[PDB]
Length: 365
Image (tube, rainbow, N blue to C red; front, side, top):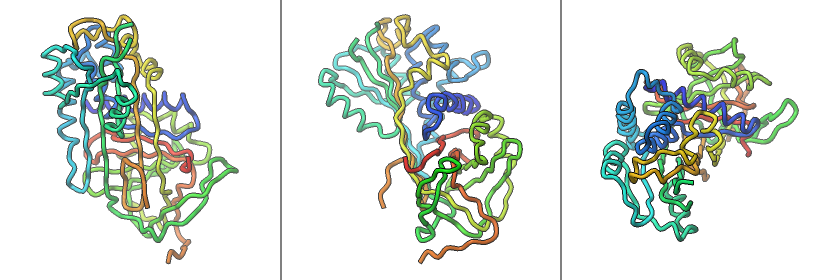
């Protein structure tokens, strides 16, 4: 169920951070989950089993069929670009001209993942690569080749997101301010702010961090976690499903005098080969790969999996795209200030799933 998608998200995060301990992180779990399951559609035996288990499903409790039904359901709900909250996701395949495929593969891909097919000419690589990159701004790509190569096809999943803050910031309350990277180093950042507000709050003394929730208009919210100084590594160590359930259950309305949140934008390009290997998905990258469900023959193998994501946080709200754009200072009562490394998780209000995960160590990066 959705407990698999959340479980998969924290497992991925732990590995990305071990790869890079002091850089910014940004990724979309549901895009990476759907792409892998889209691939597993033409897989068999051990190759199949490693993918489904790598995704954190309990096979002793769920059949393969039920798993594809869940993703079909997940796709029908997401697509809702109208109620002030825009969210969209699609799948597609680029195939080399004159490449035979099994009727069942083509059919199921269509009925379960809404996949489209495009006749592609890879012999003209430079142009074939640009077309695919332009088609996928935010998303995941799986390059498939001849067992043991060239390029037979590329599977893809893309996502878009745009939302409005339920309590907008005013461009006139944004001021240049400090942001400490270390306990003695900092940079200048546009700091937004709100005054005299009541929002859900909770102080986690166990992990030494502060949690706050800012809603968007529509069925979604953003959670911001502020670890005390030199405590990020300790919060990261306990980033598990249970902790999330506990933070969301402990939130209580409280009044704040001032809230300062930096306006930023971050993007990342990931090569996921090593990571997936660390999670148990191995055989599909070898000669022993069993992807006979695509063309009928065991002559295909996965060579490369990449993920790309962009996040923009500003006065009006949040968007998964790039940016383009008196003010008298007050200081009194209580002051929550996100002027040091923090975490941000975007989750739907009535469900236990996550659309975006990110950590901000340096906003000017």
